[PDB]
Amino acid sequence: PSQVRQNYHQDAEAAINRQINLELYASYVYLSMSCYFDRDDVALKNFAKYFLHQSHEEREHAEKLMKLQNQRGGRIFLQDIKKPDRDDWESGLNAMECALHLEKSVNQSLLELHKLATDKNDPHLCDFIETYYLSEQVKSIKELGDHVTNLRKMGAPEAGMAEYLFDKHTLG
Amino acid sequence: PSQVRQNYHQDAEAAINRQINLELYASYVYLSMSCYFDRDDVALKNFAKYFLHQSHEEREHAEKLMKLQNQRGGRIFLQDIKKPDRDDWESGLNAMECALHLEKSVNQSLLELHKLATDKNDPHLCDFIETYYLSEQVKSIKELGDHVTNLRKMGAPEAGMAEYLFDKHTLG
Amino acid sequence: PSQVRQNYHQDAEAAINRQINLELYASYVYLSMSCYFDRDDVALKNFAKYFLHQSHEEREHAEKLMKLQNQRGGRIFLQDIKKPDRDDWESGLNAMECALHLEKSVNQSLLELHKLATDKNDPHLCDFIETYYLSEQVKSIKELGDHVTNLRKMGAPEAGMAEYLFDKHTLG
Amino acid sequence: PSQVRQNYHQDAEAAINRQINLELYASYVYLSMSCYFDRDDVALKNFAKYFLHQSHEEREHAEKLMKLQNQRGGRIFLQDIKKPDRDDWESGLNAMECALHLEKSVNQSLLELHKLATDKNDPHLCDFIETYYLSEQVKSIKELGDHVTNLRKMGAPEAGMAEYLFDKHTLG
Amino acid sequence: PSQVRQNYHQDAEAAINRQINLELYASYVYLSMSCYFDRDDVALKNFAKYFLHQSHEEREHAEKLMKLQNQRGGRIFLQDIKKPDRDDWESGLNAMECALHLEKSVNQSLLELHKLATDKNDPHLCDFIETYYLSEQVKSIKELGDHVTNLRKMGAPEAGMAEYLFDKHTLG
Amino acid sequence: PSQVRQNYHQDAEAAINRQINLELYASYVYLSMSCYFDRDDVALKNFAKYFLHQSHEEREHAEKLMKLQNQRGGRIFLQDIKKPDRDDWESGLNAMECALHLEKSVNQSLLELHKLATDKNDPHLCDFIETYYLSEQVKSIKELGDHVTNLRKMGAPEAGMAEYLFDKHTLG
């Protein structure tokens, strides 16, 4: 056992490694979305900028988990980062809806992680998840929900100017 | 075909996608190395900082290739990012040697990519590879070779103070 | 032969003169587009500013080629700058599409010029074309493709608000 | 007729288009002179800078006429810009003399244009020509006459140092 | 073989060493010219300063090649720097003409070096030569050609004031 | 004889030319040492920087002698700069020892030069050597002796960490 390990259950260590992969996967998905909107036949720079920022943020979340793993004496075991389910997204609205689904999926994993930490009486892990991840996910989910709502009301993707103007105003 | 595509062979488009995956894989490997040196039983912060910086640089290289793919009218097709060949590295010297091998492997792929571009008469692609990638790889390979040389001369990993002092002086 | 001429084939000298005329012609076409959008019955100020800027940029490209011709010991032989194929353009979208066609035509000439330089083993000429022209053309073609995509999606020219809003947001 | 057109005769509109071509032609001639003095076998940097500045100024004059054409409701019809009568000028003195002849020719066209505007009772067009063109041409003609006088007195082109020193002092 | 060596042919390594000696030789020749114009019986300070600057620039070029040799894993083998063909130059014009001949000779060697790199499929070496050497040589050759042209036109060396005034104006 | 020559014996003029070659040779040797420590298999940047600085300093010494030669009315006669006795040095300690031997050899030549100047009653030459060269050589010899002493005490070259730490502390 690591000299620093204390009150860190093996299941929590394994769950953190799974969360690290999920965060890296989420970063990969956002990177794919950013590339799609940089295509000449899509050409929505702020959409590409928005998802590129999310991709970097997800990478930071994964790195923070890696720091937590080493702080508690756990050992990081990396796994393959699966490619996104699709390389050709459909529109700004569809990308936002997919991002909303992705964030809720990540949030669900964190909630399961917090439940595991609570069951193992790991208060530091519970506080770490609450302080840095649960609050961020709720904010991200709310923001994506707002974006989806506005895009739907504006008429996207059927209304051509809807995503163009949303790109300039909301994401600009 | 894309409205912007011009003198961009399909083989070059496929090769760029393969290079993008390799750059992402290289970033993943460097991230693994950075995590290893953050372990309480390794505890080499500057080694971790050095490889973390390389991981971010490799991600930037991959993103720049993605921008090139869209600029030329190609379509990005992402693939699974394979996990690093090992999660438990052995020492600062071994990590540097593995990094040196990785950089040369990436350089070889770029040289093959440049050869493909030359055979297809794609001067813009050739210039893009030369300007932003070939020069960087030579510098990175030279830097890693210098680090390996100094660590070996200092007596690492057998000499305990060798990697500690190299961490403070060269990487600090 | 001029005292400075060295490894500068006559065919390359003739090709540069042809490229100079093409660059001047491209500047003339952009000037025509800028004037069209300054008409009281078109009144798209940022469209006029955009093409006026492109016209000046094309003039700079021609002047740079003239500087290159004298640097290598070649002699500049100017030719008539043919008038643009049309004086009455149709809309912002049509002008962008025509500009996209013009840029690709200029890019094709540069690619042929680079091929000629490569066949004549003129590395300085090849590097000059790659460094200052090939990269710019790819960026210009990508930018015009993005503008055409957004204008088409917004509904131009049928949707009158499309070009007006594109004028204010993208070109403003 | 244009909604803004008022007291703008058809002949004046045609004359403005002819003047626009003449201004563009004058810019082309000055550009040719600038290139000649950039040759390695001429090498008069300030002569090249002087005529390059004149070429840009002539372009501005043409663009200002184009702005005037659209302001008054006229329609710009561009024509081929004929190449300069010669590509190989003879010396600084000869270029100045040719420039002096060119400026007087442009001035004569403007005087004819003003006479046409006066005959058609177009006070705005008359004021526009007087305010921005007639004064400039007189100044340009006087300046070129001074340059020709000094170069002739200094002994150019027979006196080798005449144009060299004139390049450094007057044009430097 | 060096741990960093990759796609670096032995012939390229030998050619670089020969180029290093040529650059050092060129620096030595320029140093000789600078000393000549510092003589009390020549007394052309700006001529001496000009050639002294060129001597330092050539030294920088040689050192940059040495850096390239070590970066690619090659080994630098220095040779005797032959003395300049003459210690007593004749005049500013003759020195410029000799410098022009020297620069073209150096340029020819670089062109041969680039051809060798191209034949060996060494894109990094080709880009290195193009980026830092071919462009500089063309500029240097053009500058020297301009200096020779002006000095000849001014009447040097028979015209006593020609080199004196050229020293003050062009080189001052 | 030169109009400025006064109390400048021919033997002194010849000796100065020999000293100029020796200074240039010393600069060449230091340049070779700097290149050696830039090798990937040596990788001692501060050692390379130290000897590169010495190479430039020796070049300045040669140029100052050339200025003195022309100042006194003598004529500079350059000779071939012989290559260094070896291209592959052995270690930091060996390079310092070789540099120490080189500096003492240069100092001995200067002492012989001063003796010749004293025998010829050339007080200006004696003062010039004392003011700018003799003091510098003693300082350089003392500095190199200190470096050799510390490197030997630290255990170099057998103790690999000795030269690494000396590179960081003394030469950093």
Image (cartoon, coloured by chain):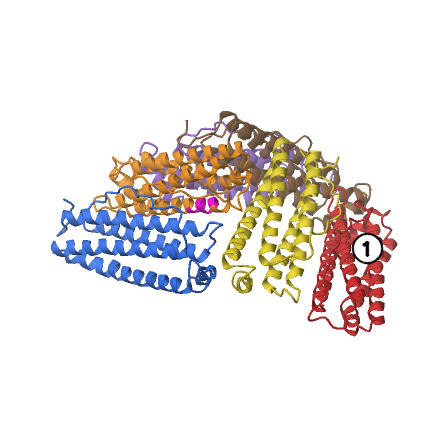
Chain colours: A blue, B orange, C yellow, D red, E brown, F purple
Quadrant of image for the C terminus of chain C:
bottom right
Residue sitting at x 19%, y 53%: A113
Q: Is residue C14 left or right of residue B92?
A: right
Please tell me whether residue B43 belongs to the stretch shown in magenta: no
Residue C95: x and y, percent? 61, 55
Q: Is residue C150 left or right of residue F155?
A: right
Residue F32: x and y, percent? 49, 33
Please tell me whether residue B64 belongs to the stretch shown in magenta: yes
F149 or E65: nearer the viewer: E65
C99 or F93: nearer the viewer: C99
Q: Residue furthest top?
A: E11
* Quadrant in which residue C122 is drawn: top right
Residue that carries the numbered disc 1 in the rendered image: D99
Residue B44: x and y, percent? 27, 45
Which stretch is magenta? Answer: B63-69
Residue sitting at x 83%, y 46%: D90
What kind of secondary structure does the magenta stretch mostly adopt?
Answer: helix
